[PDB]
Length: 87
Ligand code: HEC
Ligand SMILES: [Mg+2]
Image (tube, rainbow, N blue to C red; front, side, top):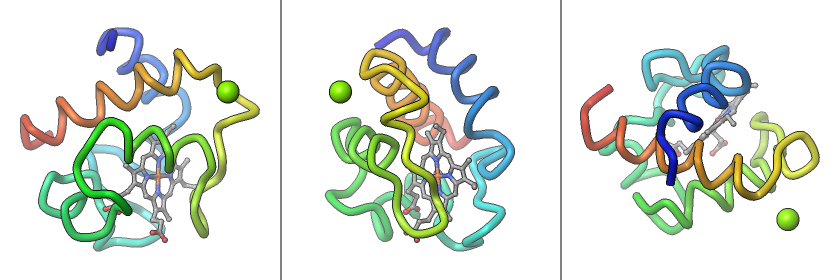
């Protein structure tokens, strides 16, 4: 994916709840690689991130209306790379 576009999408749509890769609303369920391993359905993969961004889960809204599939793929790439980089 395009992590540059991904970062822009993240700043506009995700950073309010996930700034610094954390999780405001559900504190343990962060975007850190270890938390993705534990708490994300399907584990630490771009595919699993795309699924959750697209459909939402619990307090996390769905982005399938607001974003295109390309935008979702790009933000997923950014999240995975940032997780691997420890935010
Ligand atoms: C606040 C209203 C949120 C916004 C905006 C976004 N997310 Fe989120 N996210 C939020 C919650 C409450 C949770 C936990 C859901 C649950 O109950 O299991 C999440 C989870 C994620 C995850 C998985 C993290 C983990 O399990 O450790 C990912 C990968 C994720 N969220 C990504 C993400 C992106 C890329 C967003 C912008 C498009 C985004 N979220 C918005 C809360 C909120
Ligand atoms: Mg679609």
